[PDB]
Image: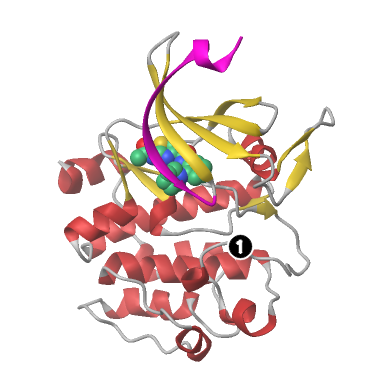
Amino acid sequence: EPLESQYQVGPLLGSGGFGSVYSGIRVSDNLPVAIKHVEKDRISDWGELPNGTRVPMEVVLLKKVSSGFSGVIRLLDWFERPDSFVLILERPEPVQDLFDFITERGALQEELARSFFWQVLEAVRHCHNCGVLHRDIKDENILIDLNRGELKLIDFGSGALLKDTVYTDFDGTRVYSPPEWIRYHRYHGRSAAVWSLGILLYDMVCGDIPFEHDEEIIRGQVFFRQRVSSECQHLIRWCLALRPSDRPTFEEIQNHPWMQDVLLPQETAEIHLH
Ligand SMILES: CC(=O)Nc1nc(C(=O)Nc2ccccc2N2CCCCC2)cs1
């Protein structure tokens, strides 16, 4: 029944705005888990469960996306403590986040970037079908299951319920945020997500993000720092179109010529991660 008896705490995986995440083991079956602690005072968005209880929005969002597709890190359990909330999440073993993977390897081969990008599109697409907008799609929030060659989305703490009306709040990564956000502090769910996907694709094929400052984002001129194919450049520039309405839909991204003949996750691992 308690968490200190049910779980076995290991080293700290990371800490920030999310805020403290530890590696752990579910003592019952020795299942590798992640144990996330967050203070109640350090919580911005709150939501209600179907049974009507005050929980952080992140618990609401994770519950909606946590059955049972391997594209998102599933919420296995959660506890409420007097001054904090404790989240028990899946933890792949062996694992490496996409950020550390690009740092170590540099710009990824187009074949590996295709497999990876398709998997995030399938994951993001799963989230929207569940009525969840991630709002912080970036290299740091993508984990690679090194044995299966499968990508997993983490951190729904900047997220929101997906809607068709304007969003006036944002607390994700600035350098991944669209020009509408920077200029007008207003954006729409799917087109903002497609902009961040273009930022991510550039990062995979070039080994770094295309823009650092507000004026670069606002200008939207894409300079390619590495050799990238005409088709991949076309997809990137389309995702990063200044006018949200000019951006591709998820269907348009997945039907793009560059996006064809994607490797399966297991062959991705056997060719690129072995
Ligand atoms: C290396 C490794 O096994 N990392 C893992 N991170 C998670 C996770 O859910 N992450 C998480 C869940 C909710 C908010 C933020 C995060 N973090 C964890 C620290 C790194 C940044 C994202 C599960 S396993």
In this rendering, position of residue 97 left or right of residue 126: left
Question: Per the image, is 188 magenta?
Answer: no
* Quadrant housing the N terminus: top right
**Residue wearing tag 1:** 171
In the image, is 93 to the left or to the right of 274?
right
| Amino acid residing under circle 1 | Asp
Eyeballing the image, is 263 above or below 187? Answer: above
Q: Quadrant of residue 26?
A: top left
Find residue 186 and report its horizontal and vertical position in percent: 70, 75
The residue at the point 44 percent across, 59 percent down is 138
Q: Is residue 7 magenta?
A: yes
What residue appears at the point 38 percent right and 85 percent down from the top-left corner?
A: 222
10 w.r.t. 39: above or below = above
Between 265 and 107, the one lying in front of the other is 107
The reply to whether the residue tagged 1 has its Cβ within 8 angstroms of ligand 1 is: no
Near-viewer residue (179 or 130)? 179
For residue 186, say whether it is visible: yes
Q: Residue at x 40, y 54 (%)?
A: 140
Quarter of image, ligand 1:
top left
Query: At numbered mark 1, what does the secondary structure look like: helix, strand or loop?
Result: loop
Location of residue 169 in the rendering, given as x and y in whole percent from the top left corner: 70, 66
**With 118 as the anchor, is 179 left or right in this view?**
right
Rendered position, 109 above or below 263: below
Report the magenta residues as a range.
Answer: 1-17
